[PDB]
Length: 80
Image 1 (cartoon, one colour):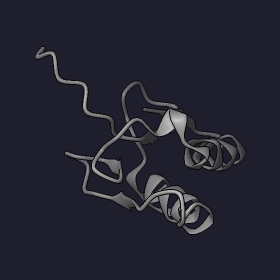
Image 2 (cartoon, helix red, strand yellow):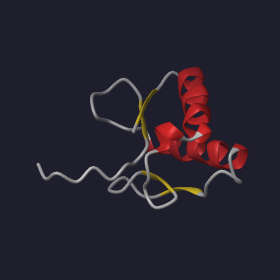
Image 3 (cartoon, rainbow, N blue to C red):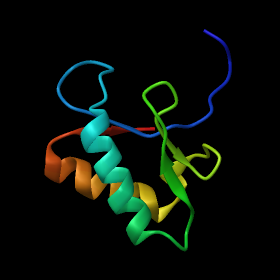
Image 4 (cartoon, helix red, strand yellow):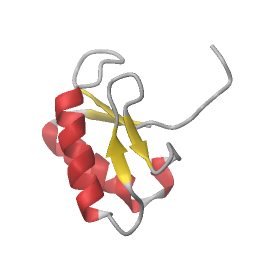
């Protein structure tokens, strides 16, 4: 590949490297809702995925913990 690791959040459901865009859109919304004042999180279509601010590393932010709490509950695998 190319050494460009611009972060994007995705929540996969079962299938390898297969994000569920519907649930991820919902999870990212909920995440953004909770962590609005932390960072503007926004969902972008399946080429670009869920972007945190400009596509920064979400793991650092509490928003990621929110994304995780919802993905686990929804039985999905949160990646970023």
